[PDB]
Length: 291
Length: 8
Ligand SMILES: [Ca+2]
Image (cartoon, rainbow over all chains, first blue to last red):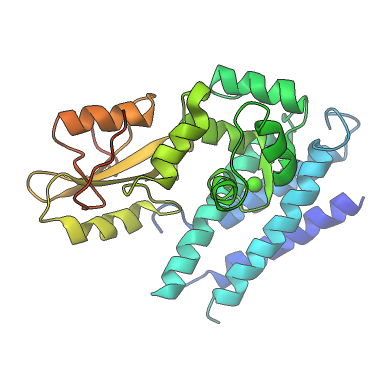
């Protein structure tokens, strides 16, 4: 197979990068590179069997892997071009988050090497039904098709708003939306019936939202606000995908981070405003009205 | 641990 050869090439590229990264808190390239390579070897061995490939055609296992491996190559070239034989720290942090996402997606859809994209179930039932009714057995769609299918229920305005949506949904920055990425998005921005209003209120129009930040980056950022107890920001958790991590400055100026209950974020923020904890988004004066 | 309890 061409696919066999592509998988071989990917494993070799991640071994090069692993060796070039020999010089720690999650997400860490040092951890993720060999973990991804080990998972790809498992996929390679599993693809050698008859069936188990699931329902065929666009958006199936073979399509997913063609797109995933091409993206993995592009991301791996970015990391290589950056590594020596702070801008660099930020570029590598963003790429670590992307690699954490690519590993989590491959583990979700090919655990132990074995494809389950046609059986995968989303966490929120309304979103699960939308995916299976709209996309069928497929586990992956190009962005443009996904925007169109999503728009049967939740249309987004073309241009900057749609592009911001794409940036939020596309965890792996591949240009394609997997059923795993849609699971994460619909958990973060529940509840379903107002999905894109929730996303506009939280991820476009809220000063407390940060995208693609690590735990250590939020610990550093909020130190600017340590003399303003009540200051807070929120960002997606890197290690518990689909959940929020709220960073806030406590009464004594300590920067803490907490993962909410499985509740709409708007509710968690409204209750924490009432209780006097989440008051000054990103340390700014104006807390937006989430009613 | 990194992630602490709900300040309420
Ligand atoms: Ca993607």
